[PDB]
Image (tube, coloured by chain):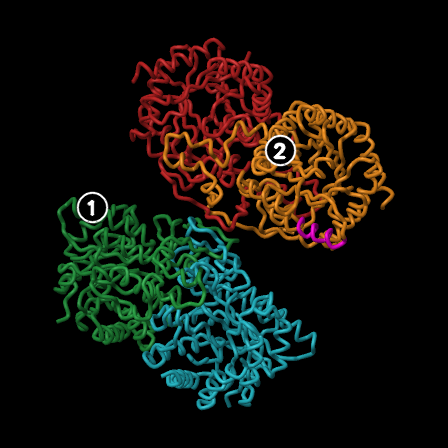
Chain colours: A orange, B red, C cyan, D green
Amino acid sequence: AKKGILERLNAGEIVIGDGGFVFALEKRGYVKAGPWTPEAAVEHPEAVRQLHREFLRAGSNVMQTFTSGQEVNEAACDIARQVADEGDALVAGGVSQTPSETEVKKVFLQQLEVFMKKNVDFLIAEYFEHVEEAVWAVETLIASGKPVAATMCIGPEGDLHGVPPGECAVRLVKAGASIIGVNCHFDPTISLKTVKLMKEGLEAARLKAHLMSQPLAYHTPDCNKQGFIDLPEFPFGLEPRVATRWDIQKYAREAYNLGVRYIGGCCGFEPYHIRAIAEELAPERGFLPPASEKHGSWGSGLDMHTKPWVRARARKEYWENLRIASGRPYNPSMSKPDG
Amino acid sequence: AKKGILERLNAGEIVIGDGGFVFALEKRGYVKAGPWTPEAAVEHPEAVRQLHREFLRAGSNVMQTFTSGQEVNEAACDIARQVADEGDALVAGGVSQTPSYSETEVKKVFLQQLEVFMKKNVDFLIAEYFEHVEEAVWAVETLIASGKPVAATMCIGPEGDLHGVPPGECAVRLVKAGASIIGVNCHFDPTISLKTVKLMKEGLEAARLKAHLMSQPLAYHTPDCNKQGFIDLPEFPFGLEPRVATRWDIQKYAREAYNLGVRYIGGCCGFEPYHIRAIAEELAPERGFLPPASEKHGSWGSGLDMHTKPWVRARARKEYWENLRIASGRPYNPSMSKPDG
Amino acid sequence: AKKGILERLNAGEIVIGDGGFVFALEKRGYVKAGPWTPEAAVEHPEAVRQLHREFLRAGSNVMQTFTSGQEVNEAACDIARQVADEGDALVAGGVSQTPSETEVKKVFLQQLEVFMKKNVDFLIAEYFEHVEEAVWAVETLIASGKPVAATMCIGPEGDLHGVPPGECAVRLVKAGASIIGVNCHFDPTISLKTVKLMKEGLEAARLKAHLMSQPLAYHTPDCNKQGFIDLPEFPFGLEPRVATRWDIQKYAREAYNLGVRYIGGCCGFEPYHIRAIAEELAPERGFLPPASEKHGSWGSGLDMHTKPWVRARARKEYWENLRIASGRPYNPSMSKPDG
Amino acid sequence: AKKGILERLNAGEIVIGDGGFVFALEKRGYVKAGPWTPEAAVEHPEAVRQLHREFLRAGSNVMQTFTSGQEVNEAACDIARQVADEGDALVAGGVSQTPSETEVKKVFLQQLEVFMKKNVDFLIAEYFEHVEEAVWAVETLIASGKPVAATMCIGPEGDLHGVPPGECAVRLVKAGASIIGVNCHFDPTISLKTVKLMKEGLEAARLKAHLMSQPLAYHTPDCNKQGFIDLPEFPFGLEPRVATRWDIQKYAREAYNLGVRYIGGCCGFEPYHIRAIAEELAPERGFLPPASEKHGSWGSGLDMHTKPWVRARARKEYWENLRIASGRPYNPSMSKPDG
């Protein structure tokens, strides 16, 4: 009786997605930074499995596959299915930007072949800068008869061709995508600007769909149209920009009020970020994730402490209004994109 | 033929220690922040085991155990021994400050703890988290009875212990108690920690009391910390993400500690497998080898030479990342904060 | 043979204007912050005269008057004329917003009476949030037969009514204003965005005019549409935001390349800022201001020093590429507008 | 009946000193940055006189002279005496580091000759890195029979030889100096650390003297023992570091509680900073300075605005507990000294 993705969304439930998986495996020594290739699926099944289980414990209702050769993709799907069966989670399929229509759809169908062999609960089109290739992806994938979702790494200023977010969203829903939204390249506020534009565009064309936000965990108020790749700090300097469990716990509420129901996360997101999403959205979802056992609510777990200040740090007010410090006073608070 | 801790140190080798274990299991949902209890050792052996293995892959030569009650400590020791046997690493024992503070009862707690680590036959012991040096000396005394190498660390800054005992006096008093390795752990970022360790080195040289030096600093940057370390910063525990070091800051602390004469170069709260991998990759040309996890990393961002853009391809060199002045990304935030305490 | 404002501009010359005059008399104890009244013109003629002479020495070619009641304005104009005659400067007239068309034009005409009595070389309409009142300004003032200039404190998002900057510019030039531009409420980059929009709008309608930039000396990258006044630091907290002689020496070149020829400054501008404008624009103007005798070019005057670092600070490269430090690490580098 | 410096101090009164005079005339175009020479005293007597009068209006009770050769010094003393006679102020002499004891005392005596001709109400030894030359100064100057004061630009880590500040202070009191303190090179907080050490050292030796503080107006938390001159921002990049009228109103209270009664200011201090000192210390001195007429108390003058927030900014609570913003988010909040 595992409800499908569209059944959950249409019922009005929040479908929390897993965080940045290929970024969490790079800091854990299994992915390399620059090829970002998922060999660890076959080389280190225990690492990939444990990250999946940590995300499931956090509150993710989706186990996106970590996708030698198609053997790696297969093994990734078996690990994802194994972990998904342990909880209220759905295995998802992911198709990403190809590095002509005939060849792009060739690549996309060869990829989709594996996800059909493995019977993934639903599919995702993601990492798409251009929306032309994104609609090609939604077309090639909805032939499966499985729910398809389309995400782009495009800011409020539209795709690389220049197509505005609203036009991109309506073009994706037209192609068949039952869920649409933004992933990667921008922090949880610019992303929710793009998703609001997408909602408005879909309401303009009366093209009902489900909304989906998977932003960066980093703060990038100094990013140009080219996301956070062009920041001088990418990839090995973004530790300061990482969000806290309060920033993400604010983006969860923002995205919920904006009308997003597939509230997840991308590069920089960790299990505790996803737990922040789940704990924020708990009073609507009617439950708390498993990992909430190893956590209070708004730092409520520190109100048995030996010091008065650390004891008083345990409340929503303190952590919501606190202005955390960079700890790097010889560094600027913003940087010019290199590109 | 697994060399012991003192054999490695006396041979001149660097003994890289594991990073903040309790802190890395809190962000992974297995430890709670505030009780900081290792209830995950029996509840989630796979999580603790995988963190141990990630640290081992990073380059750690020490699996400090993740230490009802004695059952949890035992299970932690079996997991640590399991992972240690998979590589060139040693299980370490850890005894820490008691919540109380008389000699007979503190040494009672210390001996009961030491019983389990004797049962499990840990390769060496650590006295750590000691604000006072009186209790740290008690620790070295109670633990060296094992006949195993004992190490002593305190979370004390350049201004001495809570009683005001200067770091050099602390180092001398610990080495006198029998501790073959002494150092500093926690409560301060790498530079303040390595200032304290410089003071300890000088103090030991003053009394001609030879010992091995050890540094397990915070991964956070805390230039605004008072004598009470990072715990009194308003951001602790759930606001320290900005302060987290990069693989370049830790890769600088590794060289600083090596030049300072520290050979047990590890890490504490905030340290992650990639930080320990930074330590190992920095100290590689001396150790004569690179850690396993270097297979999934270039040297100074070299792996980004593949990229399709010139401003992400030229990022692949020592100069760029060693001289880059990274940005906080929070321009509506101060770069420093006043300790609440 | 003192060339008029329009003769200077039409000849292609740069007409450097004076800096923030009532803000520089508040830090000198003669103006009060909050009423911002020019009572000091009759109470302290020597202070107002010396500030005028400092600006004239800096390089200003415009001695805007520091304008009971009409007596104070007359005294201000006498001092301005006295100091203008000492150099290559023109006395300018200033009409500003009134705290119906008939009553507003009444106020404007009563003001203009004094400036006609004193025969000011040209007039300025300035500090106009709305462009409905600014066209009334240009209308009421061009009846003098004197050159009239119109400025608003409006950002790139238009006036308070919502009129875009380009429409404001064309509507001011239609009213008769021979010079148009922006003054106050934004730093020297947002201001030069608005002036770029004004140039573009004038070129859209073929409505030739002269451009004029009088920006804030403060840095306000965190300002909303209500200028710098709504920042929490206004008025007594803006010392950190103050520009250096390099920031202003860069805005001078920006405004020159943008096509602005009346390059001056508003609140926060000091004699050394105007001297920075003049020294930057010197190679075109063909000369240097008097105050350059007490200054080097890009810190060249520090070549005398005994220390090697302070000696090497004497370069264009060093001072143009240096990221100066706030010196307040317990302070945020940006702030949310209170309004 | 103009009370002398020692009569005021011994009576328990606060003797507010003028601010950075050479530095204020550099921003006004009359002094050059790098030679820092006073030739404006004869070239521009009106500028020097107006700066003197602005400082006197602020609340300064001392009119330190602005000291072609000794003619410049005589003109400076004449202007200082002229302005001093207009209020409750005292002309003060000043001797600074030379660029052997016999030759140093020769130069110091040649200086003191002019101040004896002009009859300056008291003398100051200042800008002394070394305490050897500083005690030589106090020796050569106390022969005048006039009160002598000694200040050094030395931080909490002692003079350049290494003499601790307590030893410096006692060595200066022994030489005869009736007032001792610190001037320049450090912000108001480090300076007051040094003055605390001097007070403690004098109390160690039972060597009673009057305490004096003339700190920088800049914030320099990132300065090493060589003061602010070694910062990369010196001289033309210190605008961000400038203190506000609230920071100086805090330093005034600090110095008063520390036991300092000659509370003034060095480089970076302006008439409004000295007015901040005077307004802060008013409820003890029993009066407010003249310039307080053009100022409220803790921003009270903004009660007249039309906006609720700009009206509510008028509060001690608001301006005392406000973290002002640098407005430069692409710049670090601290910088490494270049020396």
Q: Is residue A114 left or right of residue D180?
A: right
User: What residue is disc 2 on?
Assistant: A24
The answer to whether A326 is drawn above or below residue A301 in the figure is below
Image quadrant containing the N terminus of chain D? bottom left
Q: Is residue A229 left or right of residue C186?
A: right
Q: Is residue A328 something that shows in the picture?
A: no
- What amino acid type is highlighted by mark number 2? Ala
Q: Where residue A290 sits in the image (x, y, percent)?
A: 58, 27
Circle number at residue A275: none
Q: Nearer the viewer, residue A288 or B115?
A: A288
- Within 10 angstroms of label 1, few (less than 14), some, or many (20 or more) residues? some
Predominant secondary structure in magenta? helix
The answer to whether C223 is drawn above or below residue B301 in the figure is below
User: What residue is disc 1 on?
Assistant: D200
Tell me which segment is drawn in magenta. A195-205
Q: Quadrant of residue B42?
A: top right
Q: Is residue A44 something that shows in the picture?
A: yes
- Evaluate if marks 1 and 2 touch, with contact meaning CB atoms under 8 Å apart: no
